Image (cartoon, rainbow, N blue to C red; front, side, top):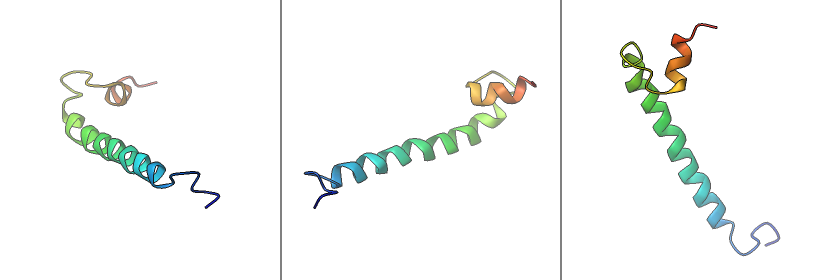
Amino acid sequence: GSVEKLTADAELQRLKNERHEEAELERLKSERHDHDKKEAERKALEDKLADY
């Protein structure tokens, strides 16, 4: 396996966890979305406020 390079499994594993982080942020922006009017939870929310 020229693509394996010892472990292609390890890469698909990292990618699997990478997506976990991305799906969490998906949910985070959903929850915090109502909290932006109260506080700038995160720049992704603060930007919406920061009309530029």
